[PDB]
Amino acid sequence: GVVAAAEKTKQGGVLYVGSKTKEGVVHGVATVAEKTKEQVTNVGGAVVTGVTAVAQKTVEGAGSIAAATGFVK
Amino acid sequence: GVVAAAEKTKQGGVLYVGSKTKEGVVHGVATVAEKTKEQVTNVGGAVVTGVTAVAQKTVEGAGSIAAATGFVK
Amino acid sequence: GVVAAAEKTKQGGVLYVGSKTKEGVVHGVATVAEKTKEQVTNVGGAVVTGVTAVAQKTVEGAGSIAAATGFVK
Amino acid sequence: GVVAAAEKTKQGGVLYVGSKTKEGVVHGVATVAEKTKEQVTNVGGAVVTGVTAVAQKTVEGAGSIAAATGFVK
Amino acid sequence: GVVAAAEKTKQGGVLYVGSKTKEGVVHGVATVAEKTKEQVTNVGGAVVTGVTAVAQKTVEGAGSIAAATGFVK
Amino acid sequence: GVVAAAEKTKQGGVLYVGSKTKEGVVHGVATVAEKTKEQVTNVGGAVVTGVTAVAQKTVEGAGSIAAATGFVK
Amino acid sequence: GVVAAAEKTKQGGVLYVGSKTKEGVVHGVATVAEKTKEQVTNVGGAVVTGVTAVAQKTVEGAGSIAAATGFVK
Amino acid sequence: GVVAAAEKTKQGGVLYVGSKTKEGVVHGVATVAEKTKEQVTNVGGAVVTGVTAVAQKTVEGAGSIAAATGFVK
Amino acid sequence: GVVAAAEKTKQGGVLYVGSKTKEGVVHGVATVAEKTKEQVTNVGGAVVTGVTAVAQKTVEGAGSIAAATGFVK
Amino acid sequence: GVVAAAEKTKQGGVLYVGSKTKEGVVHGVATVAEKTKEQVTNVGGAVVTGVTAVAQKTVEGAGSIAAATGFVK
C-alpha cells in the first residue's frame, strides 16, 4: 500500500540581484554510484540550479510523496 | 497498491536580476551509475536549471507522487 | 493497481531579466547509465532548461503521477 | 490495472528578458544508456529547452500519469 | 487493463524577449541507447525546443497518460 | 632573402599490425582560428593521418623549409 | 636573410602490434586560437596520427627549417 | 640572419605490443590561445599520436631548426 | 644572429608490453594561455603521446635548436 | 648571437611490462598561464606521455638548444 494524497481547497517590495562572476561550475541534486541494485528520484518540490538563482513564493502548497523500495519477502 | 491522488478546488513588486558571467557549467538533477538493476525518476514539481534562473510562484498546488520499486517476493 | 487521478474544478508587477554570457553548457534532467534492466521517466510538471530561463505561474494545478516498476513475483 | 484519469470542470504586468550570449550548448531531459531491457518516457507536463526559455502560466491543470513497468511474474 | 480517461467540461500584460546569440546547439527530450529490448515515448504535454523558446498558457487542461511495459508472465 | 636549398647525391624483418576498433575520430595537423591576418602551412615532410597508420623508411632525405612572414617595415 | 640548406651525400627483427579498442578520439598537432595576427606551421619531419600508429626508420636524414616571423621595423 | 643548415654524409630482435582499450581520447602537440599576435609551429622531428603508438629508429639524423620571431625594431 | 647547425658523419633482446586499461585521457606537450603576445613551439626531438607508448633508439643523433624571441630594441 | 651547433661523428636482455589499470588521466609537459607577454617551448629531447610508457636507448646523441628571450634594450 503505497498511497499518496494531496488536497488544496481555496474558497477565495523590491528585489534586486546583481551578479558578476566567471568560470562557475554548479551541480544540482546529483546521486552518483557504482554497482547498485535500485535508484529512485522523486521531486515533489522545486529544484533551482543556476549560476544566479532567485526563488519567490515557489513551493507554496499541497505536496505529497510516498516511496517504498525493496521488500524482498 | 501504488495509488496517487490530487485535488485542487477553487471556489473563487519589483524583481530585477542582472547577471554577468563567462564559462558557466551547470548540471541539474543528474543520477549517474554503473551496473544498476532499476532506475526511476519522478518529477512532480519544477526543475529549473540555468545560468540565470528565476522562479516566481512556481509550485503552487496539489501535487502527489507514489513510487514503489523492487518487491522481489 | 497503478492508478492516477486528477481533478481541477473552477467555479469562477515588473520582471526584467538581462543576461550577458558566452560559452554556456547546460544540461537538464539527464539519467546516464550502463547495463540497466529498466529505465522510466515521467514528467508531470515542467522542465525548463535554458541559458536564460524564466518561469511565471508555471505548475499551478492538479497533477498526479503513479509509477510501479519491477515486481518479479 | 494501469489506469489514469483526469477531469477539469470550469463553471465560468511587465516581463522583459534580454539575453546576449555566444556558443551555448543546452540539453533537455536526456536519458543515455548501454544495454537496457526497457526504456519509458512519459511527459504529462511541459519541457522547455532553449538558449532563452520563458514560461508563463504553463502547466495549469488536470494532468495524470500512470506507469507500470516490468512485472516478470 | 491499460486505461486512460480525460474529461474537460466548460460551462462558460507585456512580454518582451530579446535574444542575441551565435552557434547554439540545443537538444530536446533525447533517449539514446545500445541494445535495448523496448523503448516507449509518450508525450501528453508540450515539448518546446528552440534557441529562443517562449511558452504562454500552454498545457492548460485534462491530460492523461497510461503506460504498461514488459510483463513477461 | 627567403632561400631554401636541398641536395641529395647518391654515388651508388616482419611487421604485423592488427587493429580492431569502432567509432574513431582522428584529426591531423589542424590550425583553427578566428580573425587572423596571415596563415601559412608548409609541409616538407610526411603527414600520416589514419585510424591505422603505419610508416616505414618515410622521410629519408634532403628536405628544407624557409618561411618569412610579416615584416611590416 | 631566411636561409635553409640541406645536403645528403651517400657514397654507397620481428614487430607485432595488436590493438583492440573502441571509441577513440585522437588529435595531432593542433593550434587553436582567437584573434591572432600571424600563424605559421612548418613540418620538416613526420607527423603520424592514428588510433594505431607504428613508425620504423622514419625521419632518417638531412632536414632543415628556417622561420622568421614579425619584424615590424 | 635566420639560417639553418644540415648535412648527412654516409660513406657506406622481437617487439610485441598488445593493446586492449576502450574510449581513448588522445591529444598531440596542441597550442590553444585567445588573442595572440603571432603563432609558429616548426616540426623538425617526428610527432606520433595514437591510441597505440610504436616508434623504431625514428629520428635518426641531421635535423636543424632556426626560428626568429618578433623583433619590433 | 639566430644560427643553428648540425652535422652527422658516419664513416661506416626481448621487449614485451601488455596493457589493459579503460577510459584513459592523455595530454602531450600542451601550452595553454590567455592574452599573450608571442607563442613559439620548436620540436627538435620526438614527442610520443599514447595510451600505450613504447620508444626504442629514438632520438639518436645531431639535433640543434636556436630560438630568439622578443628584443624590443 | 643565438647559436646552436651539434656534431655526431661515427667512424664505425628481457623487458616485460604488464599494466592493468582503469580511468587514467596523464598530462605531459604543460605550461598554463594567464596574461603573459612571451611563451617559448623547445624540445631537443624526447617527451613520452602515456598510460604505459616504455623508453629504450632513446636520447642517445648530440643535442643542443640555445634560447634567448626578451632583451628590451
Image (tube, coloured by chain):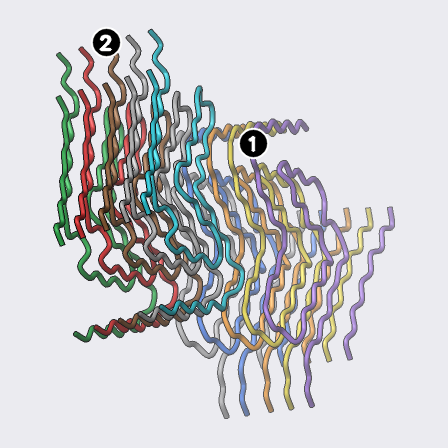
Chain colours: A green, B red, C brown, E cyan, F purple, G yellow, H orange, I blue
- On the question of residue H68 being in view, the answer is yes
Question: Whole-percent x and y of residue E1?
Answer: 33, 15
Give how far apart the Cα atoms at labels 1 and 2 are: 40 Å
Q: Which residue is mark 2?
A: C73
Quadrant of image for the N terminus of chain I:
bottom right
Which of B51/F44 is in front?
Answer: B51
Q: Are marks 1 and 2 in contact (CB under 8 Å)?
A: no
Q: Are marks 1 and 2 on the same chain?
A: no
In the rendered view, would you say F51 is above or below E24? above
Q: Quadrant of residue B39?
A: top left
**Chain letter for mark 2:** C
Question: Whole-percent x and y of residue I20?
Answer: 42, 29
Which of I40/E18 is in front?
Answer: E18
Say which element carries label 1: loop
Q: Quadrant of residue A18?
A: bottom left
Quadrant of image for the C terminus of chain I:
bottom right
Q: Residues within 10 Å of mark 1 (few under 14, many from 20)?
A: few
> Which amino acid does the dot numbered 1 rest on?
Lys
> Which amino acid does the dot numbered 2 rest on?
Lys
In the rendered view, would you say C33 is above or below B48? above
Question: Whole-percent x and y of residue I44?
Answer: 58, 60
Q: Disc 1 vs disc 2: which is toward the camera?
A: 2
Q: Which residue is mark 1?
A: F22
Left or right, G40 with reference to F22: right
